[PDB]
Amino acid sequence: PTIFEERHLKYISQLGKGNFGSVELCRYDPLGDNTGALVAVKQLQHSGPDQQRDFQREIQILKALHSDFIVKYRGVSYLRLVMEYLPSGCLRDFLQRHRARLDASRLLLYSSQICKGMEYLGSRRCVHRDLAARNILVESEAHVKIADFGLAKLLPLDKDYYVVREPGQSPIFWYAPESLSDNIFSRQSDVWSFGVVLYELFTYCDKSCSPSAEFLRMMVPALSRLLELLEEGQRLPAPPACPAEVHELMKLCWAPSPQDRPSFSALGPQLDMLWSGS
Ligand SMILES: C[C@@H](NC(=O)c1c[nH]c2ncc(C3CC3)nc12)C(C)(C)O
């Protein structure tokens, strides 16, 4: 169905928290015999008008999204958002656990898939606003999908950037400088963040060389310091054993001015080529 009755959705466990919402593992069990399919169900835990309306927009964004590389909308219940459940979890944990199996080629396959999904999102005029390996899900050994559209905004036809009034609440190390300074978000700031996702992929989300840990190594409010470092042209170093051509792609995504960063549609072919030569 595209409309699920709540009485048929049976709670199993919590999948995650964040942005005043929660994602739960539920079984859709209209027969009530534990034979129904599993689904991920997002609900708000706050009745305030601003976040209800936000959550409604999130449901409409995802509903209108159709891509092998984007978590699938399944329907709603009335208040709750019903999505496909991916038991393999987020790519961040997947990379940490299967490190020894996943070679460079594989990482480049994941990279190309995220890029393809972001190119599509771009065409819908959708800014994701929170790209990070924690928000990428694993469909299979050779298939990933972008998720968490809790902060995603649709760009008006007349603008190509979005300005957020309140400060961001995500780890600061995935933010573009223009986001840090002016809360400007666009498809090009998504490109910046995708640079960090590339870094996460090629460090297999290892905690010791995380964006977090590397900043503390490079060393006043942390946010200002981060802006300073990036202003000087300090960047994250090549992940250990990273192919040079991949690191250069990262640095391109980390171009100080948004209009100097490659598009996802330009990034895509490069990744596919690197993957075919690995
Ligand atoms: C991106 C968010 N996840 C989702 O929206 C999900 C949608 N279907 C899913 N299936 C499995 C998972 C496992 C990782 C738990 N997360 C999700 C969240 C931040 C809760 O992981």
Image: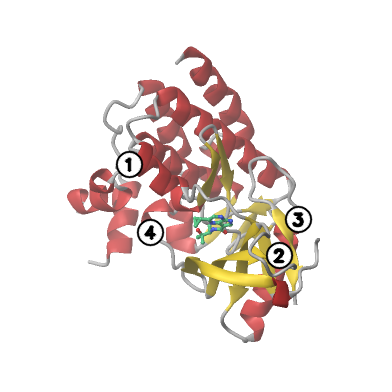
The answer to which of 237 and 198 lies nearer the viewer is: 198
For this view, does 12 lie left or right of residue 228?
Answer: right
Q: Residues within 10 Å of mark 4 (few under 14, many from 20)?
A: some
Residue that carries the numbered disc 4 in the rendered image: 172
Tag 3 near tag 2, CB within 8 Å: no
Q: Label 4 is placed on what type of residue?
A: Ile
Q: Measure how far apart labels 1 and 2 are at the Cα level.
A: 38 Å
Residue 81 is situated, as x and y percent measured from the top left of the image, at 68, 67
For the residue carrying disc 3, how many other residues have a C-alpha within 10 Å: few (<14), some (14-19), or many (20+)? few
- Quote the CA–CA distance across marks 4 and 3: 29 Å
In the drawing, does residue 89 fall left or right of residue 210? right
Residue 58 in view in this figure: no
Closer to the N terminus: mark 4 or mark 1?
A: 4
The residue wearing badge 2 is 59
Q: Residue at x 74, y 46 (%)?
A: 66
**Which structural element holds mark 2?**
helix
Q: Earlier in the sequence, mark 3 or mark 2?
A: 2
Q: Residue at x 29, y 53 (%)?
A: 212
Q: Which of the two labelled residues, at mark 4 and mark 3, occupies the earlier sequence position?
A: 3
Q: Secondary structure at mark 1?
A: loop
Q: What is the C-alpha distance between the residues marked 2 and 4?
A: 26 Å
Q: In the rendering, at what x and y percent does residue 41 appear?
A: 62, 66
Give the alpha-carbon distance from disc 4 to disc 1, as whole Å.
Answer: 17 Å
Q: Which mark is residue 140?
A: none
Tell me the residue at 45%/23% (across/down). 105
Callouts 2 and 4 close, C-beta under 8 Å: no
Quadrant in which ligand 1 is drawn: bottom right
Q: Quadrant of residue 104?
A: top left
Labels 2 and 4: the sequence-earlier one: 2
Q: Which mark is residue 158?
A: 3
Q: How far apart in space, not on screen, are marks 3 and 2 (Cα)?
A: 23 Å
Determine if residue 243 is in view.
yes
